[PDB]
Image: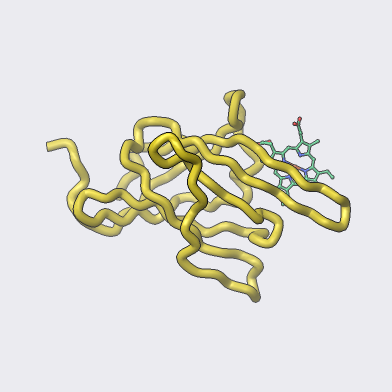
Length: 123
Ligand code: HEM
């Protein structure tokens, strides 16, 4: 009654900071709306990642464990990539962590972020 039947959908997301509720800078890197692919009731979120060379790690939590996202495809001419992960409950705010490395300025950082999916946006 409540599930999404198998299919390739769209869903809008916004990225929030790890411990604060504020738009996250990742909103200018992670592109919405994400693609949403359903197979056997396995909900898969996938989207484009720009400036992909500086986002050298991107993980979201899976079953208590922060797990590194699955790159589906890359574009080296763009300096972007396409990543995928599963989200079982899209109501809950998805936890994620990104490591940002910008070698020339010696910027090496690791941040907490969270994804907020808009259910009413599915199509
Ligand atoms: C691809 C390039 C960059 C990305 C993706 C990035 C991303 C982020 C993220 C996600 C955060 C914390 C979470 C948030 O604000 O939503 C953050 C914090 C911050 N960033 Fe960057 N950043 C980049 C480059 C830079 C550069 C070049 C500087 C300065 C030269 C900078 C200065 C800062 C500062 C001062 C903070 C606050 C740190 C704290 O209070 O803990 N960022 N960045």
